[PDB]
Amino acid sequence: DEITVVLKSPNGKNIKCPPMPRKDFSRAEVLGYIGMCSGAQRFEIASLKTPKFGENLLKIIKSKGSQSFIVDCTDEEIDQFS
Amino acid sequence: DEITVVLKSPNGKNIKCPPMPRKDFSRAEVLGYIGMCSGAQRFEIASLKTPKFGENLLKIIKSKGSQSFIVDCTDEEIDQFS
Amino acid sequence: DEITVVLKSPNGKNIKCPPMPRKDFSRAEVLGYIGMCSGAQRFEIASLKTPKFGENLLKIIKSKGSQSFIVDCTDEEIDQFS
Amino acid sequence: DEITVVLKSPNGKNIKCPPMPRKDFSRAEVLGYIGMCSGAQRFEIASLKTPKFGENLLKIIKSKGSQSFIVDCTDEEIDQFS
RNA sequence: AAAA
Ligand code: NA
């Protein structure tokens, strides 16, 4: 399949990481793709701490077809991947 | 199931990471959840070096139902996730 | 099998990481081998952000025999692993 | 089983990480255990770059009983885990 | 290596 990790701030700013196959989808892989987007500096994303993220992840785990995984950044956080 | 990683200092301070399913429970995933709690700064937790941690982990690996995994922080260490 | 991660800048500079078996080949393992090459400092590689990398990875996933995985570094990036 | 990662410098200095079960043994897990020993600071170990490490790892992967995995540190490197 |  394909799963596109999307960094999104309430701006409406998008950053679409290259897609990953559903076979590979996990929490580790999602933060793996984001780290690749941000580079050598470790990133900060407050929303990772919240339970939504884990629910939104289990949600896509149980879906059909190609999906898009949204990860919520502040307007300040999303400038790490710009 | 659910497994809640709990950061706990001898204060009695709790920090409950969002739960993870038993299917996903591992050492890598536990430090993964904690890192998400601490953010972009790598954390220090002395108790990770001790064999208790590994035993306490194998313990929960072999349990039934939803469990809670306690990770012991100094009173100073737990301020990383506060 | 064997899969040799090769860091390559348009110079034509090679850096060959020790090989990994196809059974172990993944995105996580590739960045794992590179990190081992670079050491304690987190590395920067711009090409990781691009979709080529993910395609070039799925490509080798679906191959026979021993392959070589090329990872494109700027001429400045490849000095991290030298 | 058990597999004890041992940091060893030519001094003869030992540092024994808590054991891991053979079911869990990998390159990722070995550097995972070492990181836990070193803490919040990323560690440097030159020997990780060499092919010996990968051979010495495949070696233990194909063994019976409980083994000990030796990781070679300079006399200066081993002070990271002391 | 906890995102390598
Ligand atoms: Na990792």
Image: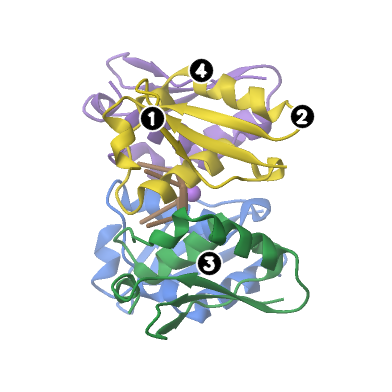
Chain colours: A green, B yellow, C blue, D purple, E brown
Kindly report which numbered mark, 4 or 1, lies closer to the viewer in this rendering.
1
Q: Is residue D19 left or right of residue B62?
A: left
Are there few (<14), some (14-19), or many (20+) residues within 10 Å of tag 3?
many
* Residue at image mark 1: B13
Task: Using the image, tell me which numbered label, if any, was put on residue B65.
Answer: none
Are there few (<14), some (14-19), or many (20+) residues within 10 Å of tag 2?
few
- Element type at marker 2? loop
Residue type marked 1: Lys
Name the spot of residue C31 as percent of width and height, x first: 46, 58
Q: Is residue D66 left or right of residue A52?
A: right
Q: Nearer the viewer, residue D40 or C79?
A: D40
Residue drawn at (31%, 55%), measured in percent from left and top?
Answer: C42
Q: CA distance from mark 3 to mark 4?
A: 40 Å
Reply above or below: A39 against B65.
below
* Residue C68 position by quadrant: bottom right
Cβ atoms at labels 2 and 4 below 8 Å apart: no
Q: Is mark 1 within 8 Å of ligand 1?
A: no
Q: Is residue C30 left or right of residue C66?
A: left
Q: Earlier in the sequence, mark 2 or mark 1?
A: 1
Q: CA distance from mark 3 to mark 1?
A: 48 Å
* Residue at image mark 2: B64
Residue drawn at (28%, 68%), measured in percent from left and top?
Answer: C77
* Residue at image mark 4: B52
